[PDB]
Length: 128
Image 1 (cartoon, rainbow, N blue to C red):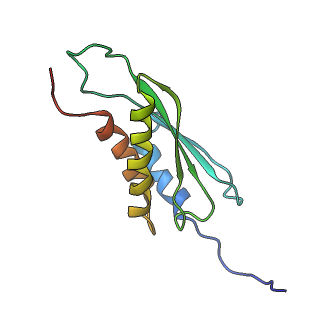
Image 2: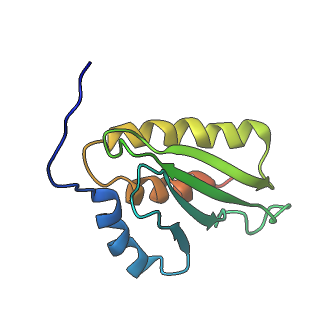
Image 3: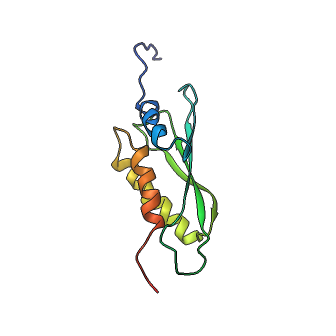
């Protein structure tokens, strides 16, 4: 039997987004949720800017981020929808890599970082 709570409700998640939007006005979408014990959702479109000469230049994936309530305390579950162009193996490699980055940026704004990787990963070395 334990209850009782009071104080100011703060949240960096919604504090950073305001800054991100300015940059990713449309590039990135954010579904506000009046920060009511509800996990925020963020979408974005990324493409590999490396495949120029090689074949199958067609490849894109929608990065979906679900920021829970704990956040930043908790890392946003990184998911991928409509994973086209990329293979099961690749897709996973994108979930694992990002997965960590999330924790590496705990305690403060991370959404920014996460997104960054979303690009780097897609891109790779030069081979022909």
